[PDB]
Image (cartoon, rainbow, N blue to C red; front, side):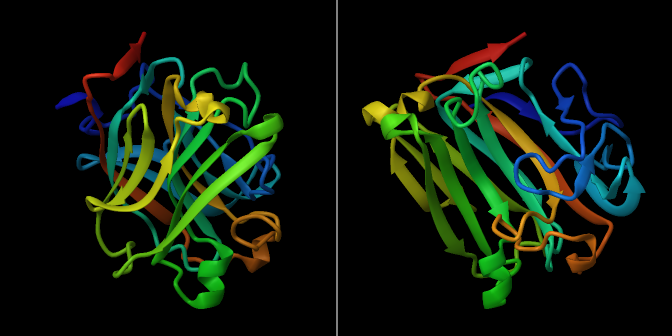
Length: 254
């Protein structure tokens, strides 16, 4: 039961749904890409959203990309949010993500607002083990016991290289749990009824981006332009993102 979607049908991204995070300051992870609001980095084509990262001198940075979200226009509490995505070859350096933040962000600071990562890929452990386009993760980041940053991360090794075709990345979010799926098969689950996880009983909004690099101690392990060996331009195709409603689903639109 689809109650909200983006099929990316038109020729331009709908600004009455989406907003652009603009900047090249690393976004708290030492990321190298400058996220812009340009057609070069984010555009619609043949029923797909395309976020394109490029090796390119821009705004002090050596890479451009995009980082888009629906904060203020679309949020929801409880439901199945699924996206059909063909991630680019992350090789070494590219870090695409499909994830959500609490709808009180940025008024409530991170991680108290709450974070749910549905898809991350291109991690340093994946590089080391030679599973660049196979090893993914979901994650929960929040303010737990003592209001302290708590990270729950579940790793999965996909059977096939996920950059070769579109795959379905989903979260199922109920009053009791958050579950994460690849092509309908669960690879992550956490109970969210605990008192310190009340941040996951508010509206959240989705986010899509393609980061390039990070601090050595961060996700990719590759912190300079010269260490990025991935094919550029790198394109993430998103055929659609849909919200499958639950009885308990609260929809927020403006």
